[PDB]
Image (cartoon, coloured by chain):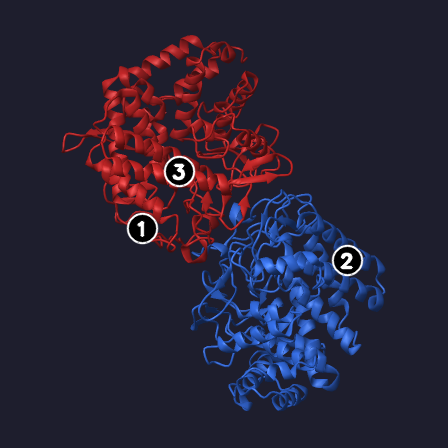
Chain colours: A blue, B red
Amino acid sequence: DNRPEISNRLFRSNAVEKEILRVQKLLKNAKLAWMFTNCFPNTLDTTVHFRKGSDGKPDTFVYTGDIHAMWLRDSGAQVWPYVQLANSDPELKEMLAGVILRQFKCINIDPYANAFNDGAIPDGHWMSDLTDMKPELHERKWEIDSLCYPLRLAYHYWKTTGDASIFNEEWIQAITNVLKTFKEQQRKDGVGPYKFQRKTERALDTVSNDGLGAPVKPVGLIVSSFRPSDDATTLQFLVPSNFFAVSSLRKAAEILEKVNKKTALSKECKDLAQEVETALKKYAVYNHPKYGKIYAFEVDGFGNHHLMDDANVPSLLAMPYLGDVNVNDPIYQNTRRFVWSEDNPYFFKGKAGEGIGGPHIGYDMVWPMSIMMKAFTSQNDAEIKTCIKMLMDTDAGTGFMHESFHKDNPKKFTRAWFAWQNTLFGELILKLVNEGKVDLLNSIQ
Amino acid sequence: DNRPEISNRLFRSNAVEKEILRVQKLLKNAKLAWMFTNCFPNTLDTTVHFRKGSDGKPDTFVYTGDIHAMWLRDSGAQVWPYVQLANSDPELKEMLAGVILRQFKCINIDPYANAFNDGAIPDGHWMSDLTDMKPELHERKWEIDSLCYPLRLAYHYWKTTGDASIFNEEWIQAITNVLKTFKEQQRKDGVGPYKFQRKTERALDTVSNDGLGAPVKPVGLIVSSFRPSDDATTLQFLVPSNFFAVSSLRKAAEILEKVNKKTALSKECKDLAQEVETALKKYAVYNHPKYGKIYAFEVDGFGNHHLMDDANVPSLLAMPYLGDVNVNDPIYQNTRRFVWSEDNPYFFKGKAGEGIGGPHIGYDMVWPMSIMMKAFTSQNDAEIKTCIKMLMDTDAGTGFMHESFHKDNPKKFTRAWFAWQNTLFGELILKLVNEGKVDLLNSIQ
């Protein structure tokens, strides 16, 4: 396999190793078993720094891979599929708790920031951004989903393990920050305190209108300055992220009620979730002449819509994966047909495969994430099989998941070492195995 | 008045001076007569460098004013209102021929460029832009309207004066270049030869997707990478510019047939104009739930629309002014209600005035150009009066037209010296006088 040598692996989990052995024995396709082995543990192998803080509480720093900082998004997804093993592995469990606690610490340092350093560093590369940068931050691109992924992870950890110890005063500070930030970004009474520009040739790495972005009408939705691709939004009410905020606020509300016994703060979360949900139903649905009612990718509240999808989760395609809409919501099913078609400007189809990319890497570059999400949200084995086959056929022989690959030639690719994507691939294969679809995977020749 | 001292004025026209005295003696409102005197001749006073070329032919270089280079657009507009005087003033007429011939020379240097130097400036400010630069260019932002404005000026010059001497072999080369460039930018067979990025904090001064912009589907419309604001397009089929291309190609078709006797090249212009017109009819009309059928500001050919307007002409509001749609086109009339409303993200209304701006200067900055265009396309004297009074009341006492002013405070403004806008003001007042509406202007206290 392509895992690091054992002495070079950063974090070892007995339960992860045992699960790798179990899947290896069930899978008859050698390439698939190998890819699983490379990818499922890649986070633990290459990105995880577990320790105890000054207070004796667990603390885990998680790098993205070939970008050396911790994203709230990537870290929340990178350890996600390990939660289901935590009850059998105390060391794994405490590492997970450490991730969540480190995420809350990040939110409290700056709830607008997407990417964090492990303490202060000097001469950070993005210190020159025209925004309120600090040495503790790697980057300060405001992305709604940065605040959702930790809530998601914390809720699943708590439900799985029963361990409420993570919901301490730093949690209360973090959810209080999440509420403040989301409300600022509804922009009801003014543009808010967040502004961003950067001197760059990359148009989506800076923000129009002196760092405020295109105007929005403050109908109750939350502005996301940037997408989970880290690209600026076009119309600033980013729809899949708003849907993720609704779910995440409701999870926070349940924690605050049942664990913290803070019913006022719980209600603040539920009320905001409801406001956003009501506004999404009113403003985010577009009567498409070909596909019927679909969800727009972005809106501005004035009546504009942006009909497309980007591979990064939260995306329109992946909403049932995160649990933000039902997979059988008829509007979602119409949307799924739309995003996976040449009516979507960021859908590409070529000699080697097809799928969704976006403006991050640009034309003709398909993201394995989109194909994985197509599989995650599929209700048909034949569709799932085409997805897994394509993921296997587009790795350029590396045994790993990439950011993107060229539609006509998977040897042209980006990000060799992208731990979130490796985690997702392991998660997908493990899901299929656990759902009784081993025979389906073994039919891949 | 605020004109330069006589000995500092760059170009003198007898006919212009006579019209100023005419208007001064007719107008009872002293501030309006003073504004006309400041504004109407501003281009001649401050931006026109007329000479005889080595070859005998007139040549006129026209600076924008407080930005020091020649735009195809600005130069085309700056001298526009003088054409009506050309039959009375040989020196003015020759100067106007020289603008046109200089414009054709510019187009032949680079038909993608918006802005030109008077000769070569190898260390020019923008020579570092990530595009194919030449020292003769000030800036190389691809704007469809750059190629339209010279065609419009030449046609009006020819129709007014009868002088076809401007339609020489440099003209043939220029129109050939226009056709070639427009067709490249339909992107039927690939993305074309034009790409642009710039390292800048200003998001709309560089272009997404590695300098290609957001994908379009090649339905027959022409891509404009930038708008007449010099801001990058969002969806790249810029609708008012496409409508302007239709009219301009049809003017070029007439000239080529009647003057040059080139029936094939004439037909190529007619056929392209028709292709674009048919595509506009099929793709640029949006069924707005409030306003009815309207014209989108931009489309991508996939089914996306961008519902807004920007002050800069060509704009949706200004289409009847340029002659690209009839003022009583019902879809235009719906569009006009839409663009001058708070449903347009770039319409602003405050304590001092109201009107359309754009992302160039950003939030709450109204451009006098929009108010002027509302008056140019008005069919009601009361509306015209309100616009003239607003122009007078929002000059911050300078006696000149600005780029933009704050909706609550005209003393906060941009571009003190903007010759295009000054010319346009003088054009507007002279139009109203020549239409017999001086009593309307005299009713302003």
What type is the residue that disc 2 sits on?
A: Cys
Report the residue marked by disc 1. B127
Q: Residues within 10 Å of mark 1 (few under 14, many from 20)?
A: some
Chain at tag 1: B
Task: Confirm or deny contact between disc 1 and disc 3 (CB under 8 A).
Answer: no
Gap between marks 1 and 3 measured at Cα: 37 Å
Gap between marks 2 and 3 measured at Cα: 56 Å
Name the outermost residue toward the left. B55
Q: Are marks 2 and 3 on the same chain?
A: no
Report the residue marked by disc 3. B274
Please state if B55 lies on the left or on the right of A374 as rendered: left
Q: Give the image location of residue A225, x and y in percent.
A: 58, 54
Q: Quadrant of the C terminus of chain A?
A: bottom right
Q: Residue at x 54, y 59 (%)?
A: A341
Which residue is more in the foreground, A247 or A332? A332
What type is the residue that disc 3 sits on?
A: Gln
Please state if A137 lies on the left or on the right of A249 as rendered: left
Q: Secondary structure at mark 3?
A: helix
Q: Give the image location of residue A348, x and y in percent.
A: 49, 62
Q: Secondary structure at mark 2?
A: helix
Q: Residues within 10 Å of mark 2 (few under 14, many from 20)?
A: many
Report the residue marked by disc 2. A269
What type is the residue that disc 1 sits on?
A: Met
